[PDB]
Image (spheres, coloured by chain):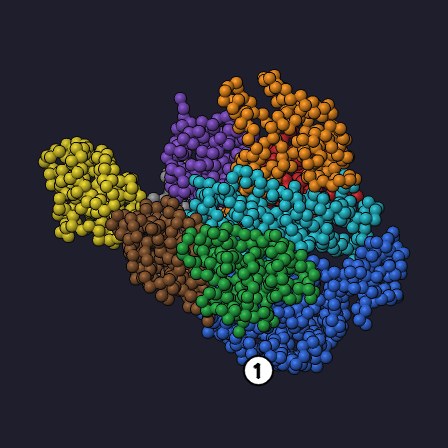
Chain colours: A green, B purple, C orange, D cyan, E blue, F red, G brown, I yellow
């Protein structure tokens, strides 16, 4: 069938070995076609744990994690960590929609049990300091989207939204 | 000696009974508290145009009015707003029939036929500076009665 | 709102005054210069430099010769070299019009935004739920004077309060974002 | 003067963001509504007005009245395309306005929530307003001093408030937005367009055949050319409050209300938007 | 408030229209308009409702009364629609029409100081700007869209397309008076854009028609029933009509690629009925499915509940005209090639067509048939052919050979229906052709004839195989 | 001999109301009365004035019924509902311009039929712009009131 | 310390036996005092699993569940399913807040794994059929609040805001 | 063709046996369905003749006699005293109207001679006396509209209708 | 059919064992809602007959009695000292009233014979000497109202209310 992996886009670097499929199929939800990114996905009520980044659940409607959607299984390290779920492709709040939906998808989101040990307060984060933008454009946007450097020289066009689009929330304690 | 308070009492008896729903009463009370200051500032003819424009003078409502002039068992029917505005129009016309400003036969014969409500308004226009002076105390009385005998929303 | 041609810089809007308003501002300044040990001779001198021309439309800072103001009024202007730069900071021109032409321009120069109320049941507009409101365009300038009587607190007021007072909310429709205002204190504007 | 009239279209074509579009459309409506007369050798005898092409074109040699009618319909479509192409967006004044306003409000100790929203389809806001109403019969909610279409703050607040009612009961709705005996705890601003891919306005059409018709013998199309807001046009607006526990519903409602319409005739998928961004800047 | 039911649909050779009357314009492309889908759904709903109310009570209702009846699902000026349409095209991104350059200024020289018509023709794979004043020049351009050389000859052969193309093909320039190269260049530039945009015909448009239902409209009085009938009619619209222009001649013909229902209690009886079309082996199978879904409503569906409400209004058979489906006329065939069929529909529905010429002779009945079933047709009171012959054959009284007799068509006493059948320009075609497909390459051809209220006891027996022979010849 | 804006509005409405035979035309003129005044503020008087003259579609024979409406109280505006409502409101406005002596009836008529004078009318209207807009919206407000009063809600 | 637990209010009620503690202290968060039900919690991005009722993590923010907070410890066989957070009473998307809270607490919410082998097709559900209203009034609002039917008769308030406040999204399948 | 008959509705119940044609045609102008009477005719100037009430024409526009207009012809033994005319159904005073009319009609108005031998000075009188509204819904409504007490049963509305709608000026002389 | 019995309040306990049905239905008219008594009824023209205390019917509109309106049925052996009425919730003279009634209510009032021998000279009586209302609350507002000893210690509010709101007119014999 069709399964997707939620690669959130923080300013952390702990997302190196995070896929068990590079492309595998011929269907990525997030795309780039000479205008920018597409189908960026937002999950509210979740704060990443960038110190070993994982989607921690808070019940706050004002948190949000934005990321890209790729296809595949987690790592061969699964079954305890990710919050996998099967959604009918209409439960997805996709920013910059361009295509259509498969009408049902399997999503894996790198999830962490809240660890109810501290008041899990959080703080918003914006992706600045293009250094980290540059290194993530190699880390993910050449490792997943090797379509870079094949046609896409307007990386600064994409780098623009990377510096703008993928804001998120993190506990930062 | 003040017979405008007496005339006001009679008109208020009529309208207070001619309104079934309580919301219609309360809407009339608001019209009473507002249109007197309006008729003082802006004058009689502008305010009259305002009232009659928010009254919905069809041949049905006008019939209820023409009967109200004699019935004691008539009823003002319609929406709270339309009936409040028509009740205030009745207040005013009732003052004009008494005090002999307008001949009652003329007022009735004009309320019936649409080709003569314009002539009603033309006579009202010619007389406006007289009406605007006389009716002041009548309308203040109606205001006081309304804010006494009716409650607020 | 202006439609000008034959002019280098293009303007989507311009400031408009009449000589009646200027006469009223001058009157304010005269009155409060008599009633107090205060005299704003710079502002007064600019105002009556303008008022000298009373009787013909002028432009303080532009090369506008003709224009159509509020798409209704065709005015022929003729410049004046005064250039009040501190009230009209952004280099917008400032037309001072004959009081009979400028009343119409000023009065159609407002915004009538017509609103409604929706009937949540049917999700159409309620009956009788439809009205207009006048707003005054943003960047509009009103002139006013704050006067004080000799007291110990009035000094404390004019020195601390009126010096930290910059923004207020005036009027209604605050929750439409319709009240925000900046006070200027001619004490440091002219 | 009649010269402003006979040159308004050249003006539109040559200034294109620095004319007052409101007055420009209103003045060219006089040309539109006097078409048959501005053509009777009143082209100003210049060769720049788009009126000169209607002296060459011959649409009905046999009757000049039908001829002028057809030329006028062509002129209406041409004006719509002219406004759409030429009048485009500079969002620099709008960015300056919103940033200065954020500063002002931070001074006043408000909790600001900057919101941007890109239009996904062709939008239609204030379709009963007055901009083109005298040419097209439709309007667009349009600021004549920012010279830009916009979304009224009352309208955004109304949609948010109706959503919050549907979601949380009218009691809590009033607790956030106030009733006739209290006042709203949350303030909204208009939404002005800050950035667009391309064209700002684009022409569209509606053609009622069987609206208000008894039978098929009534049926006759009635096309309605009008201007709409182009897709991929971003609208920025703020939300500011003091009471902290007003942040939760608002920033929760905003992502959803946008998916459904935020303008006119959204039951045929017109005025859809996408949440592009949110920034809560709390007051400390 | 809640997604009711999705639909994956497919439209072949859609001829959608925009403000410029084309699917593409200098600003966007729109191959499918949700407004057209909404309006056509409403039209088909009214047709289906009259079919129902006539197959039980023999009555017919005015479109006003029906629209007022269904304004709880479809909304009116008194209520917002309960259903919200959202069309989503895949690869329906932001394209538009750009005309990078056109090499004029030689066509202009042969124009100046003259009054010349400038036709265009696009055959020969190059654009050649003919001039009525006997001059021909070929034009070189490079445009945004690429006409695939299949659409060119398709338009060339399809005598219906090549006709409605007359209105985007020429102008009548008058350069006698002062006429400068700039405005002439702009005139011909916009003429060329208009011509070139006619060729945005892309067969096989695929789109997802989502439908959201506002749950706030609870069971007010008969909401679930009205809504279920609306969904029945939406399915009947997808299975008997297309979108865009010339749908009554094959274009825009819709097809079901997939259906997904999200509120079972409502669309469960329609999602199965739609699966009943995701695979169709043979023609008679499809005809059976059609008659099943059609009869399923006339008796099997909910009941005659709101047909007994005091909101409806009987038609006046002499001043009102409605249509309604007649199940007896549902000819089906199998295509094996679509373009040829779309081309031969002309021979089917043209008064000198060699597929109806050989089904009807003496030609007057022929005219008559079209003038009653083939929409509006420019008739002339100038050369006898109108004299009597059609006037006698459409007459409801006065003879008994014409298998069609218009209700109020009088000899020399023509009052309304004569001035509607012979004078009203915007009259649809009752004889309609649709092209269906399953997910295999099984292309069929629904032929059918809508039944009109202005007929006086139509001879169903006659046209039932006149229509059959017509379907035979076009395939 | 000077009539106030309400008396003038009443005298105009009398003739219009009489000349609208069909009740649909009345009910359409009522809506014209309700909306054209806000449009006249929002877009100025000259734009909306010519909007009205075009939406009336003077037809060169309905123009003549309009012309007679100034003289004979036995005139009748004929044409479609939407045309007759707009030609009635046009009569309203022309009446204000004439009875107030802002423009002459001769010039108004000539400019209304003959097309060479239509543009001279545009010029003469731009000249008298502050003369008109100063006190016309009161007359049109009176007309709106009278219409919403003596005409039934459709 | 101070720890709560969120008992949700959907139309189907297996709501009796879920928790061991029923006192906590002299107070809970959700209250009923002379004005109706106060301090009701709204949790977005979730849906109920009324078949043995629990909360289901979803990604669609258009989903939500509303219920009340009473002090308990859920059946002491967990740290496996029933979620636990420590939020500072500001990220709490509460409704009708009348008295502030300790701002450092522990919420226990009835959680369930997504069970990702079928889609998640939710549905909005409100409350009617006053037998349902009444059986909820008696099945929980006395299970915690003995204040009803003995200290007050105002129950029409709770009889109306139950049908007003508590509307949720269910899996229905 | 189409011919109707006018019926007084005063308290003097002369409506028991005073006209003959029950229905005859498809419609009486007066209609009743769940929204009271509709299309009641008013005749102004006239007065009633309480002893066998008949319209004595006073020349006073203040005097009126509201009544109902039903299909038929009077008693087949009259028309030497009655008034009869043909007015085009748009030239007659009609209140509470429900639909449009046949655009012309013949109408038989019960008309006494003016009895101009002793003076006519009217006294306006309404309806009262529940006995009277009961006997009137007996006499005139039940035969003319048998629907009364079979299908339209809410004679509550049609009784208060006549208690408020129908009034008149009576001679009392 | 909801049935209510009126019970007076004198200064002497003529109300020891008179009613035997307390709740019966679902609600109560006479309330205690953060503000004291509510929906108290005043019957005008019926003095008190403390000696066998029942509402002796006088003909003086200036005599009146106020009292509770409990939901109950009297003794199941009435028709010997009682009057009975069914009233449409508007004929009722409620004071300090809170909640609309269901438009259908049978009322049972203590009645006594006029006994046309002893001249009815009735005088007003005003409750005081809070020991009196001390016995009242335990005999009235505790027997019928367990809201005390459960909800509040604020008996003093309703106590001063009884002193203030409740007077009556007693036949003094």
Q: Which residue is mark 1?
A: E281
Picture quadrant of residue I50: top left
The residue sitting at the left extreme is I117
Please say if D96 is above or below D214.
Answer: above
Picture quadrant of residue E169: bottom right
Residue in the image at 64% along x and 43% along y? D96
Q: Secondary structure at mark 1?
A: loop
**Quadrant of the image for the N terminus of chain D?**
top right
Residue F38 in the image, given as x and y percentages of width and height:
61, 42
Residue in the image at 70% along x and 81% along y? E358
Looking at the picture, tell me which residue is in the foreground, D37 or A63. Answer: A63
Residue G113 in the image, given as x and y percentages of width and height:
42, 66
Can residue C64 be seen here?
yes
Q: Residues within 10 Å of mark 1 (few under 14, many from 20)?
A: few
Please say if B10 is above or below E409.
Answer: above
Please say if E271 is above or below I159.
Answer: below
């Amino acid at each position: 069938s069709t399964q997707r992996e939620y690669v959130f886009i923080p300013i952390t670097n702990s997302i190196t070995i995070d896929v068990k499929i590079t492309i595998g199929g011929s269907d990525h939800i997030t795309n780039i076609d000479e205008r920018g990114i597409h189908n960026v996905l937002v999950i509210t009520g979740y704060a990443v744990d960038e110190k070993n980044g994982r989607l921690v659940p808070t019940l706050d409607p004002c948190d949000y994690v934005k990321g890209i959607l790729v296809a595949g299984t987690p790592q061969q390290a699964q079954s305890n960590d990710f919050l996998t779920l099967k959604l009918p492709a209409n439960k997805l709040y996709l920013i910059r929609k361009k295509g259509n939906i498969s009408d049902d998808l399997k999503i894996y989101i790198p999830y962490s049990s809240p660890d109810a040990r501290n008041s899990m307060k959080t703080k918003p984060v914006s992706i600045s300091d293009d250094t980290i933008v540059n290194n993530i454009i190699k880390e993910v946007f050449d490792k997943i989207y090797n379509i870079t450097q094949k046609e896409k020289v307007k990386i600064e066009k994409v780098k623009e939204d990377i510096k703008e689009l993928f804001s998120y929330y993190a506990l930062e304690q | 000696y003040e017979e405008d308070y007496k005339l006001a009492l009679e008109a208020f008896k009529k309208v207070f009974n001619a309104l079934t729903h309580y919301g219609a009463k309360q809407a009339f009370r608001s019209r009473a508290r507002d249109l007197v200051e309006e008729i003082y500032n802006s004058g009689f003819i502008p305010t009259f145009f305002y009232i009659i424009s928010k009254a919905e003078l069809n041949s049905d409502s006008l019939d209820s009015l023409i009967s109200l002039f004699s019935s004691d068992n008539a009823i003002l029917r319609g929406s709270d707003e339309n009936v409040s505005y028509s009740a205030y129009l009745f207040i005013i016309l009732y003052y004009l029939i008494k005090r002999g400003i307008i001949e009652q036969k003329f007022l009735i014969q004009a309320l019936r036929c649409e080709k003569t409500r314009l002539d009603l308004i033309d006579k009202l226009y010619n007389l406006a500076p007289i009406i605007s002076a006389k009716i002041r105390t009548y309308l203040l009385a109606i205001k006081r009665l309304s804010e006494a005998l009716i409650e607020a929303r | 709102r202006i439609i000008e041609i034959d002019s280098a810089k293009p303007y989507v809007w311009v400031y408009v005054t009449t000589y009646e308003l200027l006469k009223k501002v001058k009157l304010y300044l005269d009155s409060i210069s008599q009633l107090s040990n205060a005299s704003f001779s710079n502002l007064k001198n600019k105002i009556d430099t303008i008022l000298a021309k009373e009787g013909k439309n002028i432009t303080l800072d532009s090369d506008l010769k003709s224009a159509i103001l509020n798409e209704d009024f065709y005015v022929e202007l003729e410049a004046l070299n005064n250039k009040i730069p501190s009230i009209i900071n952004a280099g917008v021109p400032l037309l001072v019009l004959e009081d009979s032409i400028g009343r119409e321009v000023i009065n159609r120069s407002l915004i009538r935004v017509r609103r409604i109320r929706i009937d949540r049941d049917k999700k159409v507009v309620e009956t009788g739920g439809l009205w207009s409101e006048e707003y005054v365009p943003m960047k509009t300038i009103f002139f006013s004077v704050l006067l004080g009587k000799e007291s110990k607190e009035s000094a404390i007021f004019a020195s601390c309060i009126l010096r930290n007072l910059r923004y207020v909310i005036l009027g209604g429709k605050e929750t439409i974002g319709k009240g925000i205002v900046e006070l200027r204190w001619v004490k440091d504007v002219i | 003067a009649i010269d402003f009239l006979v040159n308004i279209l050249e003006l539109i074509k040559e200034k294109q963001c620095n004319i007052n579009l409101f007055s420009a459309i209103s003045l060219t409506s006089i040309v539109y509504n006097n078409f048959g007369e501005f053509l009777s050798n009143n082209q100003s005898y210049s060769t720049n007005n788009p009126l000169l092409k209607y002296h060459i074109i011959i649409l009905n040699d046999k009757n000049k009245t039908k001829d002028v009618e057809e030329k006028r319909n062509i002129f209406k479509r041409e004006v719509a395309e002219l406004i759409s192409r030429n009048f485009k967006l500079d969002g620099e004044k709008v960015r300056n306005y919103f940033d200065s306003l954020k500063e002002v409000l931070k001074s006043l100790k408000y909790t600001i929530v900057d919101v941007e929203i890109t239009t996904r389809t062709r939008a239609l806001i204030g379709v009963s307003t007055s901009l083109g109403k005298l040419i097209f019969g439709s309007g667009i909610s349009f600021d004549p001093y920012m010279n830009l279409p916009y979304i009224p703050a009352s309208e955004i607040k109304g949609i948010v408030r109706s959503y919050i009612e549907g979601k949380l009961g009218e009691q809590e709705a009033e607790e956030i937005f106030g009733n006739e005996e209290r006042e709203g705890n949350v303030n909204f601003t208009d939404a002005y367009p800050t950035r667009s891919k391309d064209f700002l306005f684009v022409p569209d059409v509606i053609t009622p055949h069987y609206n208000g018709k008894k039978s098929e013998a009534d049926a006759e199309p009635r096309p309605v050319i009008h201007l709409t807001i182009a897709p991929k046009v971003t609208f920025r607006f703020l939300i500011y409050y003091k009471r902290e526990d007003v942040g939760k519903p608002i920033c929760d409602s905003m992502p959803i209300i946008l998916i459904r319409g935020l303008g006119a005739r959204s039951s045929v998928g017109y005025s859809l938007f996408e949440l592009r961004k949110i920034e809560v800047i709390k007051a400390a | 408030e809640e997604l009711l039911m999705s639909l994956k649909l497919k439209a072949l050779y859609p001829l959608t229209g925009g403000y410029n009357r084309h699917s593409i314009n200098p600003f966007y492309e729109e191959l499918v308009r949700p407004t057209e889908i909404k309006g056509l759904w409403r039209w088909w709903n009214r047709v289906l409702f009259n079919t129902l109310a006539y197959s039980t009570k023999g009555k017919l209702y005015t479109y006003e009364s029906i629209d007022r009846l269904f304004e709880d699902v479809f909304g009116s000026e008194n209520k917002k629609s309960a259903v919200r349409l959202e069309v989503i095209t895949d690869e329906g991104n932001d394209n538009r029409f750009e005309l990078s350059y056109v090499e004029l200024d030689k066509v202009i020289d042969c124009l100046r100081n003259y009054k010349r018509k400038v036709s265009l023709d696009f055959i020969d794979n190059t654009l050649i700007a003919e001039i009525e004043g006997s001059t021909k020049i070929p034009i070189s351009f490079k445009s945004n869209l690429d006409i695939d050389k299949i659409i060119k000859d398709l338009v060339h052969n399809n005598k219906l397309l090549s006709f409605e193309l007359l209105g985007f093909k020429s102008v009548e320039i008058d350069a006698t008076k002062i006429s400068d190269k700039k405005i002439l260049k702009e005139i011909l530039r916009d003429l060329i854009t208009n011509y070139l945009e006619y060729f945005n015909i892309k067969q096989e448009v695929t789109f997802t028609l989502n439908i959201y239902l506002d749950k706030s409209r609870e069971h007010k009085q008969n909401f679930e029933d009205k809504l279920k009938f609306a969904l029945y009619s939406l399915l009947v619209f997808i299975l008997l009509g297309g979108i865009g222009r010339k749908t009554s001649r094959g274009f825009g013909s819709l097809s079901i690629i997939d259906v997904k229902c999200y509120d079972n209690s409502i669309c469960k009886k329609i999602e199965d009925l739609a699966k009943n079309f995701l695979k169709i082996s043979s023609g008679n199978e499809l005809k059976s499915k059609i008659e099943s879904i059609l009869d399923c409503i006339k008796n099997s569906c909910i009941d005659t509940l709101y047909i007994e409400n005091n909101i409806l209004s009987e038609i006046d058979p002499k001043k009102n005209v409605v249509y309604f489906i007649n199940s007896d006329l549902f000819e089906v065939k199998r295509i094996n090639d679509k373009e040829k069929v779309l081309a031969n529909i002309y021979k089917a529905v043209s008064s000198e067509g060699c597929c109806i010429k050989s089904i009807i002779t003496d030609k007057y009945v022929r005219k008559s048939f079209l003038i009653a079933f083939g929409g509006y047709r420019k008739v002339e009171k100038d050369k006898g052919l109108d004299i009597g012959f059609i006037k006698n054959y459409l007459c409801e009284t006065c003879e008994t050979v014409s298998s069609f007799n218009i209700v109020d068509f009088l000899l020399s006493e023509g009052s309304f229906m004569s001035d509607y059948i012979l004078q009203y320009e915007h009259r649809n075609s009752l004889l309609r052709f649709k092209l269906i497909s399953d997910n295999s390459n099984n292309s069929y051809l629904i032929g059918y004839i809508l039944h009109s209220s202005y007929f006086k006891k139509i001879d169903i027996k006659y046209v039932r195989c006149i229509l059959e022979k017509l379907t035979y010849c076009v395939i």
